[PDB]
Length: 225
Image 1: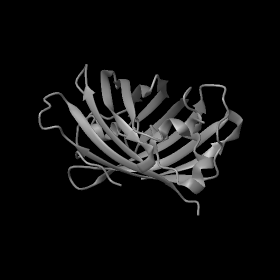
Image 2 (image 1 turned 120 degrees about the vertical axis):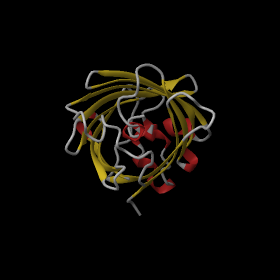
Image 3 (image 1 turned 180 degrees about the vertical axis):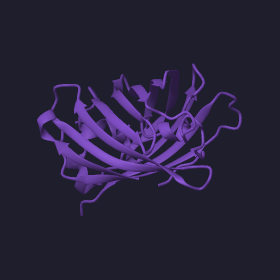
Image 4 (image 1 turned 90 degrees about the horizontal axis):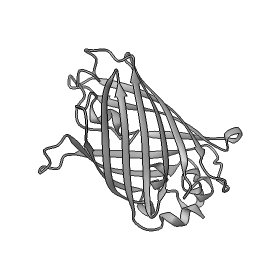
């Protein structure tokens, strides 16, 4: 039944509270998702303390329920099946030769709006590293998210690598471990192994003077014929 909530365009709200190496910050996002086309459009704004980390490092943390699952793969869509009551999404993101983020989010409907509420904690970052030193280019490389069932928690696990371009031409690797568990008591779908093919594009609003990120993202489930 959850999948029926996603047949049209759905408004999205994202709210994140962060602390990276003691630097506190907050992000508010708004936009919409159209899972029929695997399509997300979101604008994020930094609302409190100066953003202590580069915007691209926050993309994966800042609604995989908007993935396009092909018809023949619908039985594998855990994310929509948990709706409207939602799911908890937790990650550990390890930045190679640098610190880590631990994130805990709840993704659920509030009325007709899909909401992603996040707490992010970053520790062990290096002062003159690529993250605290703001050495990452404002762009994104196009990410297979590998998913498997977690039967004992009636949920899923995922793992994937993202690669963030450094201004010198090199790359900063981010290893992601992910777990999702339902919030409510409805039945959920436990998937066969598969992946999400993801492509994100970052831009700026030329009329926006606040620190911000515009994101256009397309995601399609794959790996099953």
